[PDB]
Length: 169
Ligand SMILES: C=C1CN2CCC[C@@]2(COc2nc(N3CCN(C(=O)/C=C/c4cccc5c4CNCC5)C[C@@H]3C)c3cc(Cl)c(-c4nc(N)cc(C)c4C(F)(F)F)c(F)c3n2)C1
Ligand SMILES: Nc1nc2c(ncn2[C@@H]2O[C@H](COP(=O)(O)OP(=O)(O)O)[C@@H](O)[C@H]2O)c(=O)[nH]1
Ligand SMILES: [Mg+2]
Image (cartoon, rainbow, N blue to C red):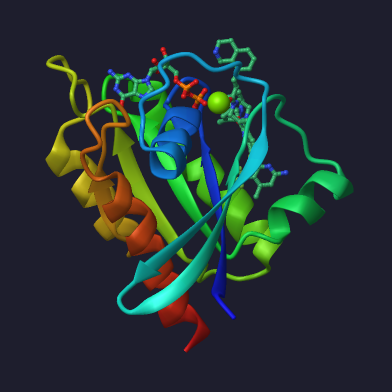
């Protein structure tokens, strides 16, 4: 069968989790999507010769730490940690997302990619070098994306898949 990869998209409200997910799956930019709608999306794609089923969870809605919520997030094999390059608070929030991911996975080594979204915008408050440097601090890859222009969208998800393979081996 297809090799399945459970990918989870996380990060602050309004960074573009939904727009990124919809661009990957449906190949168009949706600039407006209810921020409480959380759903799973699936795509058949070949990545480095391997036929893959991508199962992508677009997180949304309320922050909460029930056992049921942890159990759901725990099924993710790798995580896209998304901030917006024009929102410094979303960048500052990243450590919190990373802390929660390590917690539910019961491991200090979880496949993760730092994603700086909205790179089409002329004004930016988080420079590329600062974000590249934070990824190096964490030991994870960094990808700049725009759900609007498609820049880096495949790169970000496919890099996460490659990180999962490395962890499994
Ligand atoms: C420093 C902090 C701690 N908090 C204090 C406040 C800020 C912060 C949030 O923190 C914070 N938020 C989270 N939500 C809420 C905000 N949101 C949004 O999209 C909101 C959109 C929205 C909703 C309603 C109205 C509007 C909007 C946006 N438009 C305008 C109107 C992103 C995400 C769903 C959030 C979500 C999740 Cl799944 C998790 C998480 N949970 C677990 N149990 C286990 C694991 C492994 C994780 C994760 F790691 F895998 F993710 C978190 F941990 C989260 N954490 C950040
Ligand atoms: N310019 C630009 N705007 C974006 C991009 N991705 C999302 N947005 C906008 O950012 C806002 C929040 O996007 P959304 O996908 O709902 O973020 P979410 O809350 O993380 O799911 C909306 O106004 C989108 O139009 C992008 O790559 N570039
Ligand atoms: Mg959303």
